[PDB]
Image (tube, rainbow, N blue to C red; front, top):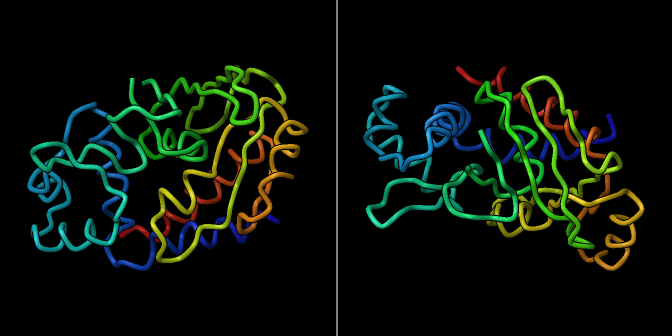
Length: 205
């Protein structure tokens, strides 16, 4: 798997803080209800002390909070982005939309616009496959996650959908200052997501 460096670095962003992996799925599953999630609700769901819940979250600097300090964004978010994820929620980046359905056990209708051209793109993402990929040649950009950097800025903001591989490569050609920038087909990107989830689940206690 020549996408192994991306999977390794993705999992690295999770495995480091002892609890992050075990907090992730429960949090996504809640956020998927479409409402803000309090630290005490989360703590109850995880059967953790609040101090532990707060520790893990403190490491996740990109976490989005509402006016009451309820969590509203952690990969999956209630606040509008370029990546629509209907089960109408939003995701931080293209790869998120490919990974989450398996983790939350739902099929999502995903839509966005090509980063290079603005053209509409959509697909349906289930826990096991992607279907109704429009356009058929849809592509995704990847960068290598940068350890300890803000994940939303260093990774998510560079991980897009494109109308086609050639269109994405043209775009990539003008952005070579990004670390480990790579263009893959959306089907390749989904497979990377599957590898990520398969490992993530093993590391969950």
